[PDB]
Image (cartoon, rainbow, N blue to C red; front, side, top):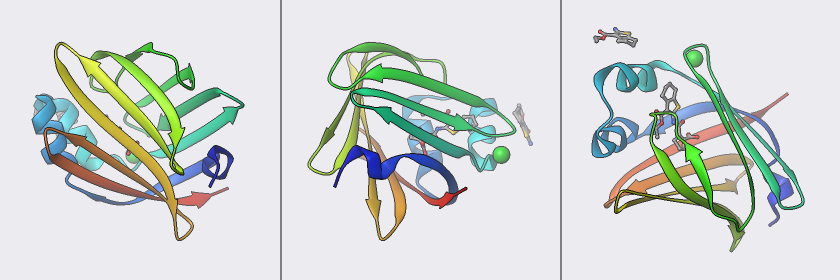
Length: 134
Ligand SMILES: CCOC(=O)c1c(NC(=O)C2=C(C(=O)O)CCC2)sc2c1CCCC2
Ligand SMILES: [Cl-]
């Protein structure tokens, strides 16, 4: 498994636990309603160690860029400013966020041809599945 295999545009086809995850983050009602109803695309590109992830929907588009292995300031879709590091490890992209004494992990892996995106904060989990599109 390589980071290249994750590249391209992906469309959300299933979500479980996302509202619970947003509540654990303390996201307010407007962004939680938007997160319930959006069906974003995720666009992953990677040029060696330069990674970009763009989340695109009619309601909100966000994007970040980083160098794998390097700490950077991420503005999240809910507006937190986290210290983030992304790495490709054990056949998954792993994105670790730390802020104000809190931490959350997001993983992205290929399973049976789908992109499986998992999030956790304090044992509150979500799984979002995306299918490859053109
Ligand atoms: C963490 C806060 O996340 C959000 O506020 C958020 C999304 N987040 C995601 O889609 C996320 C993931 C994913 O499936 O790529 C993994 C990290 C969060 S998608 C979206 C919103 C809020 C606005 C509408 C669409
Ligand atoms: Cl949408």
